[PDB]
Image: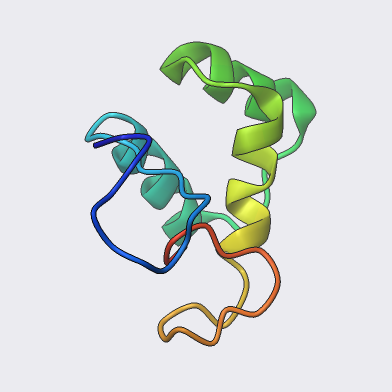
Length: 77
């Protein structure tokens, strides 16, 4: 459901719920990038790891609205 899906694409995924997807998309509209004093505070506020938040903002800047998302695609980021 959150760590699994009945499809064949990617494999290994991340699939996050409505608190997690809310905060990540709302910084992706107003910002590009978010530095360590405020990025680690966003990960402690929402409850995730520093390495999964860092590579979420890495994979979202990658020509993303098609399945040509060549390096760093965890589903369809």
